[PDB]
Image (cartoon, rainbow, N blue to C red; front, side, top):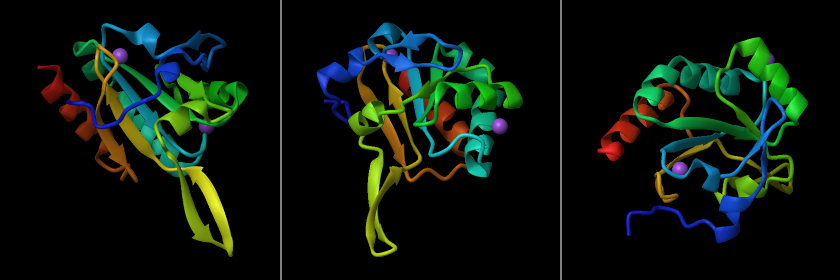
Length: 158
Ligand code: NA
Ligand code: NA
């Protein structure tokens, strides 16, 4: 009833490779809120701005018991380098095979260059403590975004 997106059951058990060398799963986050933000490419201007914006709000997400995950299809090593350079204190998922991206339907097509071109569309989601996707943002405008996500989280967590 309150879900805005339905994920295949298997999505929650996908092994998600993280920066730092461990794996997580969405089911492993049961019991707390999870923010999942998808971005197209490590170490580019918009993606760096977005990551820094979430990083600055980490104590506010903590106040709510929430965790954050950033997601792109860059490698674990790329993610480690991005986290170290920028000082990120949350993990990045290396979704190299785009399994998580496809589950959230963030791989979008554009007719460009006389081709059908597929790529990650910047998108964010709020996953409840019981694993429901209760809010989505697609074609994300980076400016103001992390603040808006935090506000929405607070409103939902009540
Ligand atoms: Na970087
Ligand atoms: Na969760």
